[PDB]
Image 1 (cartoon, rainbow over the protein chains, first blue to last red):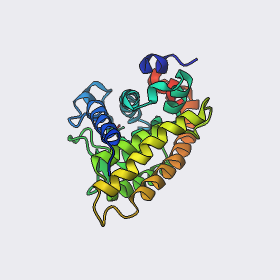
Image 2: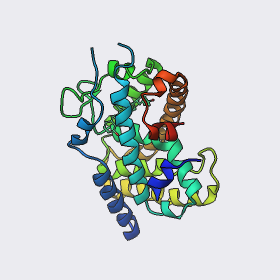
Image 3: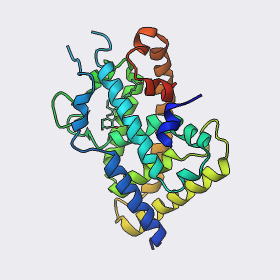
Length: 10
Length: 239
Ligand SMILES: C=C1/C(=C\C=C2/CCC[C@]3(C)[C@@H]([C@H](C)CCCC(C)(C)O)CC[C@@H]23)C[C@@H](O)C[C@@H]1O
């Protein structure tokens, strides 16, 4: 679901 | 004594924070201009600051030893729950005892109780917040203590929806045990007395503060007109 968090965490 | 691994950990967190936190506050110009004339005039400015701050918190988190071991889901959950608490914690550095406000080196970026109210937040959150800031300020912690607290907050086993409690617990223990050991070796009386227990207590106050913000956030967020002023990140993180 969460996209923006996943990208930033790498 | 402070073991070498413990000294290493402290070095890493300090550096992490120095990169993640800007004393100059230069980046603040980029946010939508603050408005103090008008309901929730402050919110667009304040919402951008929060969004910015969320990014900075995410970066700090990644640098924390063992945070990278956790499943992606477990990383996500820890950030989602703690992001408000950490922002309140890091915000202490801008907070001034004399005026009881957050001072960003300029009159325009100075933040007072009425400003936060102009965000759409009631005194019940606000008044406990200010009290927390004072109580934290009074501790006058070393910078090493300050970073360590934020990292121990970020990595919590209890947080709802955690996939692997045991592993998150293991990572937290190392940092906690690092903080305890540091105060006793590196912190002199009478400031050292009760400082770990007092610091732990502040995490409990943050949990209460998180619950209040969340309720207030949902009533704010529920209205489409206010929701439009939030950043995409803020909506995703704060839900
Ligand atoms: C963030 C930081 C700063 C201030 C934090 C503040 C000051 C104003 C009031 C704030 C923004 C509180 C608000 C109740 C937050 C409400 C957020 C929302 C409107 C979305 O529900 C929490 C933290 C407080 C500036 C700087 O210290 C960096 C730090 O990182």
